[PDB]
Image 1 (tube, chains in turn brown, cyan):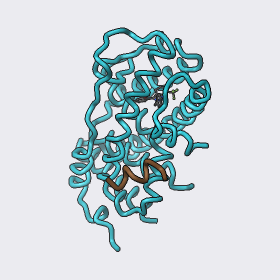
Image 2: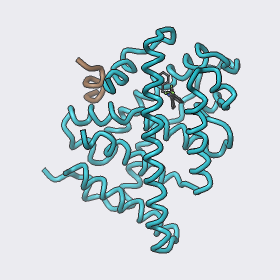
Image 3: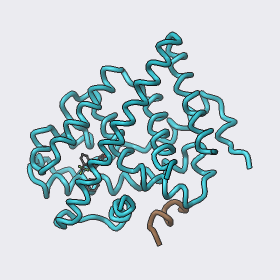
Image 4: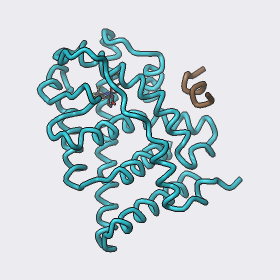
Length: 10
Length: 234
Ligand SMILES: Oc1ccc(-c2c3cccc(C(F)(F)F)c3nn2Cc2ccccc2)c(O)c1
């Protein structure tokens, strides 16, 4: 649920 | 699964890191020199917010980082982000004695740092660091190695990472040898550079305390991303 979790994937 | 990072030559490691460098972002085009908490922290927040996106994509390009689990990458970035913003700032400010180059169109002096309770001390620390870099004649290739070390080292204690760190040490030495330094000069310079990382850590810690304070004060808007990065330091 961390934004960082998403950004690191993209 | 063997990491591609360790198979790189020194020159290749250096090329990879130079190529991964984020660009230097600008601040707003308003030429008003900030002389208040609101103005200054407003501009610093916006800049930090944008730099973070470039930092995240930079980290993915640091050899070895990609071999980490997602959770480990998150932890390393959470621990290190302020140190990384700060060393970047110090590096950009080198050629500007007495000045902090937050952006090419945003240079702050210590007299402006005084505009935030508790800021001038951190400004002075940053300026002393920039001055140190300058008198050492720190090179761009050296800078990128140091930034990568911070990424990988800062959250490490909270084997692959260590091997990668050694690889970066090898690369720093390679650079000093390439530049003609004697053996003694190499180990001394290595030591000097790495000791500055202690101070960069210190500045991050103090800054984090200051940002939490500002967070609680709640006038300078913080993005959800910055809040999460900050909350990670509890
Ligand atoms: O490109 C950059 C580099 C650093 C910062 C930065 C600070 C510089 C000096 C003192 C402080 C502190 F507030 F911690 F004492 C700094 N914090 N930050 C990051 C930041 C600033 C405002 C809101 C959220 C994070 C920078 O802003 C950009």
